[PDB]
Amino acid sequence: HVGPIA
Amino acid sequence: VNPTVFFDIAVDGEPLGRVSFELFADKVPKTAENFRALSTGEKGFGYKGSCFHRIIPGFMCQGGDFTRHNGTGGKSIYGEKFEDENFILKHTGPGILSMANAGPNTNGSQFFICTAKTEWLDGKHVVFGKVKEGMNIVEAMERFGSRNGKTSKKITIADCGQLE
Image (cartoon, rainbow over all chains, first blue to last red; front, side, top):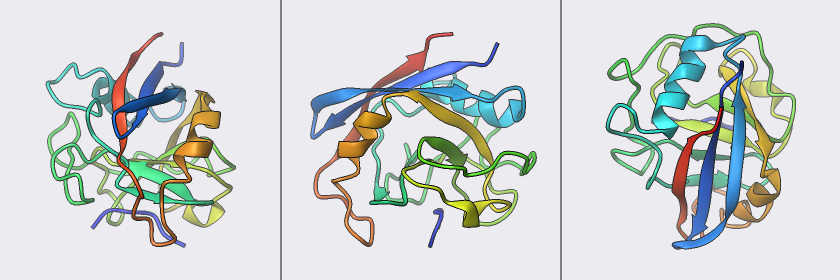
């Protein structure tokens, strides 16, 4: 569940 | 002094161009070292062949998943994940190379290349490098990613390695 957001 | 590595990008196998990066070993050694030994393959596993499963236009291009390729795997040279060495460098603009994660101290092998200033990730993601040359390749590379991030075509790391 890896990831940057916004 | 600072290590320089690169990626030869391909859009469905058809080469597009190269992208080199400067790893800030002067700020994040262990974090930088990991990415260096991953772009060369000197541990038997790395980015050559893997893809950019998540590309969000205006935001960033994410990759590093050489095991599961869907945003579920990948690993460092110290096994699975590893700690957040520090938060000194910021996501000041397009080109920035920072570590992707699933919460604090969960740095593995996934990373992202920013295509804009992403200051909200400051303090949550460890910046450890920056595109030296080839940001122009990431321009067109970024046209292959939907709002949600799912690509239109397969963006692959055709080849990669260390030059200095």
